[PDB]
Every structure is written in C-alpha cells, then in structure tokens.
Length: 262
Ligand SMILES: *C(=O)N1C[C@H](NOS(=O)(=O)O)CC[C@H]1C(N)=O
Image (cartoon, rainbow, N blue to C red; front, side, top):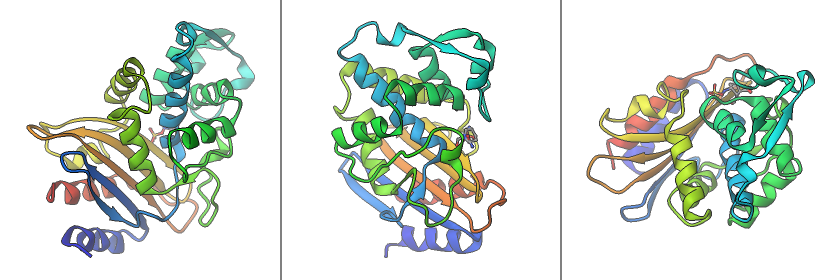
C-alpha cells in the first residue's frame, strides 16, 4: 500500500463504511486505487453513462437531441425537479440529458434509459466503449436500493474511472458529443459538497453525484487542476445499514487525501 492508500484506509475505518476510490492522472496515466476492483452501487452516477449513450446515438442522428419525449404524470418517480414542470408536456433528449446530469432528475434518467431500450442498452454502450464491469439492471428509482452484495446496478471504481476518462477526455464519443458531455458535467448543480469540497478552489471540476440506500454516497469527477493535465476521480461510499445518512464529507475527505499526492 501507498501512503495515500493508508490514509484512505484510515478515513474508511473512521467512517464506519466501505470506501472505493479510483484516480487516473492523465499527465502520466498513473492510477491510484483503493478497493478499486470492488463493486459499489452507482446510484445516480450511472446517469453519466446513459447520457453518453444518447450522445453516442446522436453521432449518427444530427437531430436526435432535439427530439421531443412525452412526460406523463405516471412517469414521475421519486426525484423529478425538472420533469415535473413538463408533465403532460414534452422534454427534448437534450433537455432530459441536462436534467439527468445537472439536476439528477430521475424521470429524465428513465427517459434516457428508455431511449436506449432499457438498462441493457446502457450496459451495451458500456461494453461497446470497453467497460466490461459496468452493469445497469433497473430503472429509477429501484436502481438505488444499493443492497450490500447485490451486483445489480454496480461498477468498480477502476472501471468507472477508466470509462469516465474515455468519455470525457478520450475518444469514446465524437468531438462535439464529448464537448457537450463535459459542458453538462461542469454545469452540475449537486457537487459542491463532494469531491469538489476536497480540492483546491482554483481547480475546475465536472462531476456527477449519486446517493442511495445504505447511506450510499457517490461522486465521479473529471478535474482540471491549475497548470496540470486533467484527472479522473471516482469516490464511491456505502454503509452497512439501510437507513444510514449520506456522508458526502467522506467523499470530500477522500478527494482531499488524493489531492495531497497528485
Ligand atoms: C441519485 O443517486 N439519485 C437522484 C437524486 N440526485 O442524486 S444526488 O443527490 O447525488 O445529486 C438523489 C437521490 C438518488 C435517487 N435515489 O434517485
């Protein structure tokens, strides 16, 4: 173990839960892993992959992101801050992608999932961009049950970091779609208490948070530190009891520990 890993272990031990971290430094492609090959429930962080999959579809349909998608009252689930304003109306796939990523709208996420033919279509996109680990099995809201030992709707920190890098910094998407994904992630509204809180204020972050049962507290981020090449950082966290409170400070602490290395 490295010093960063021993610090992450100490944070995890005092946290009362299970922490997973994966950093990729694209300055030199090095990786820091803590429980990097253990599965964690993704919860809302799976939305990135659904949005990227729709962006990928849009590479061969110029007008796909402008296509209207009907929002019915029955479509509303547990957290719909944008979709509820369009009930009995429509949202475009661009609007749904932005709502899913920036406001973590679960109705928008379900519309993205349906646009891909269900959770298996998101998993298939993951496979098509080289992610052998990601699996999406359910829609919102049950994909957030986050039951320990349940492999459904999970990934590992390493695989998620690798995928987020390919999507945001690599060529898993076309150039325009990559820029759109990064623009969406950087305009996230929900991230300031998570990885963002553990990094120097001068660094630009685009991220996607998630949370679920068992106190599951997740964040996945692409980071532009001042004067250095970007990083990819994945912090997953989950706890032993179903009603545990969210612990975004633990993600911030892990990010702060990561930041002290590179
Ligand atoms: C995603 O994990 N979810 C949607 C909603 N927003 O996520 S955030 O809090 O990480 O921004 C929170 C609840 C969760 C869900 N159970 O749908």
